[PDB]
View 1: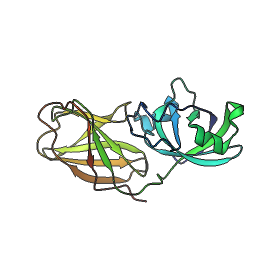
View 2: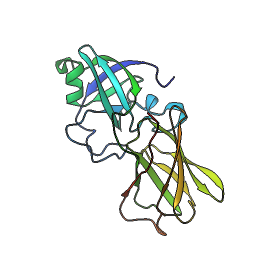
View 3: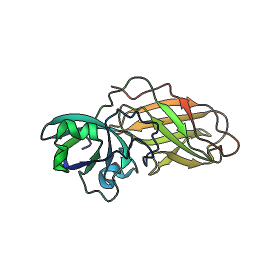
Length: 207
């Protein structure tokens, strides 16, 4: 049902390159991005399910793939708020709003995951974001005392949990198609950090 084609309208703005709700900065100024309505955003009951995903959008002039970096506040289902460069390729900007058909598509990237640890994170409370993923990340779990604890995905595109444990963290993430992948990131600090930081990933969802 995730591959299903979506129908809606699209507008444009230049607000997703910086300060987007999904905290995916920095976004290359020349990239094709988009803001997505709240309904479609939270797919499968998981908040920000499509955050960081890539959509293939088709307008009256053609198709293009966009990177979901922000939320489209009060937007209706199927509604998208594309960046100028993306909108211009599938439609006429002088039209202000265009009809579209889109669907989630494999991320046109290379490499493995990259994790972002939000400020204030530690072994007591942590928010961990997954970046550079081929498909949308549904669910993320970490291992503690031989058990896999499930982390709740938040609106700010980060998986949160408390009492993460000690030592390096063993995590496992599942995509929108049920594909699972395991990895291990360095230990979390003993006190909430002042600034967020990134940590390299060693895995990726299957093609």
